[PDB]
Amino acid sequence: PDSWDKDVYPEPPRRTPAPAPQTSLPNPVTYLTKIFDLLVDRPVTLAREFIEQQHAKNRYYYYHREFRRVPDITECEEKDILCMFEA
Amino acid sequence: TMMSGRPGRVPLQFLPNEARSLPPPKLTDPRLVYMGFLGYCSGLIDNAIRRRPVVSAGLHRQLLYVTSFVFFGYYLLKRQDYMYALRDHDMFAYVKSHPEDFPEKDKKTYGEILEEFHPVR
Ligand SMILES: CCCCCCCCCCCCCCCCCC(=O)OC[C@H](COP(=O)([O-])OCC(O)COP(=O)([O-])OC[C@@H](COC(=O)CCCCCCCCCCCCCCCCC)OC(=O)CCCCCCCCCCCCCCCCC)OC(=O)CCCCCCCCCCCCCCCCC
Ligand SMILES: CCCCCCCCCCCCCCCCC[C@@H](O)O[C@H](CO[C@H](O)CCCCCCCCCCCCCCC)COP(=O)(O)OCC[N+](C)(C)C
């Protein structure tokens, strides 16, 4: 997921070199990646799809509490307990 | 002695007529409940000293203990509230009568007030 602000959390663009083999031997890393995709990634993707389908059945929201601005200790008079508490 | 000798004080008077302008204590006052608790404890101690079943013997005398303690506590609370009200009244009267002795001071904000900072290190 990418549920965060890219400007707040910057990340330079990702440059991945293309695979250019120079030998006839097979790639064990590639074969193991295929095996991992077949055995792990697909089942976890199916499970996540089911879970997210269940979540969308009942969708509810929560909010970010906004706090008003109040006068600060510079404007507070001396021995004024309420203003001092707010500040 | 501070309160004794106050003008208009009738000697040997538990509650003067001016004390009736104050709210009487509520019968559910926590102080009255504590007085009743003291009475109940006194009844239990009486049973224990006289070698009777503490929690089941002498119910009538335990009730009398509680009632007497509640009665005296109610009157004591009335007198205490009257005395504190009288003290506050006299204090406010004197503050009104002596403004040069109790003057208002300028209120400076903390932006104007300079106070020394002591680092903690
Ligand atoms: C609501 C909660 C209120 C909590 C209040 C807490 C404070 C209470 C203070 C007043 C206590 C008066 C006790 C009178 C003497 C009783 C002695 C006795 O035998 O008792 C057994 C007696 C029944 O047994 P028994 O067969 O008749 O007597 C056997 C004989 O004594 C024959 O037995 P024995 O002679 O073989 O026994 C030998 C014993 C004989 O010696 C004693 O038994 C003496 C015990 C101490 C009595 C003097 C205490 C004076 C005040 C101390 C205050 C300290 C600070 C307390 C702070 C409290 C804060 C809440 O001597 C020794 O073991 C020698 C070593 C002594 C070591 C040090 C002991 C003293 C420690 C000092 C502090 C104790 C504080 C708690 C005391 C609790 C006593 C029940 O049970 C009670 O007395 C139970 C009382 C409590 C429950 C009553 C029923 C209530 C039902 C409804 C509940 C509703 C709740 C809501 C509404 C509430 C409305 C009020
Ligand atoms: C635990 C220790 C306290 C023991 C409490 C019992 C002591 C005996 C209480 C007897 C009460 C009798 C009241 C009946 C009417 C009496 C009227 C007159 O005699 O006294 C009045 C009221 O005065 C009494 O002294 C007040 C009685 C208060 C009794 C309880 C005192 C509690 C003290 C704090 C202890 C904590 C409370 C414990 C629960 C009680 C007016 O007095 P007044 O002539 O005009 O003022 C000048 C006299 N001076 C010089 C002594 C001041």
Image (cartoon, helix red, strand yellow):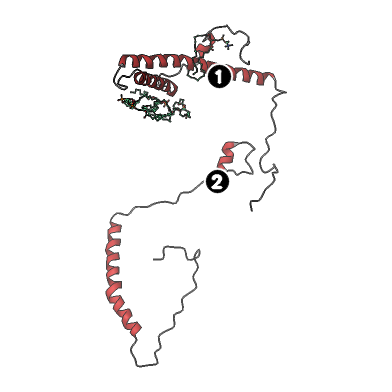
The numbered disc on residue A82 is none
Side of B45 where B21 appears, left or right? right
Q: Say if B96 sits above or below B9 in the image.
A: below
Residue that badge 2 annotates: A69
Name the residue nearer the viewer: A68 or B8: B8
Are the residues under badges 1 and 2 in a single subunit? no
Classify the position of the N terminus of chain B by image quarter: top right
Residue that badge 1 annotates: B84
**Callout 2: chain:** A
In the figure, residue B51 lies in which quadrant?
top left
User: Does dot 2 land on a helix, a strand or a loop?
Assistant: loop
In the figure, residue B72 lies in which quadrant?
top left
Side of B84 where B37 appears, left or right? left
User: Does dot 1 land on a helix, a strand or a loop?
Assistant: helix
Which residue is located at x 29 percent, y 18 percent? B57
Name the residue nearer the viewer: A46 or B5: B5
Which residue is located at x 29 percent, y 72 percent? A40
Q: Say if B13 sits above or below A36 in the image.
A: above
Which residue is located at x 28 percent, y 56 percent? A57
Side of A66 where B110 appears, left or right? right
Of tags 1 and 2, the one toward the viewer is 1
| Amino acid carrying mark 2 in the image | Arg
Q: Say if B12 sits above or below A37 in the image.
A: above
Horizontal and vertical percent for residue B35? Answer: 42, 20
| Amino acid carrying mark 1 in the image | Tyr
**Callout 1: chain:** B
Which residue is located at x 27 percent, y 59 percent? A54
Mark 1 crowdedness (10 Å alpha carbons): few <14, some 14-19, many ≥20: few
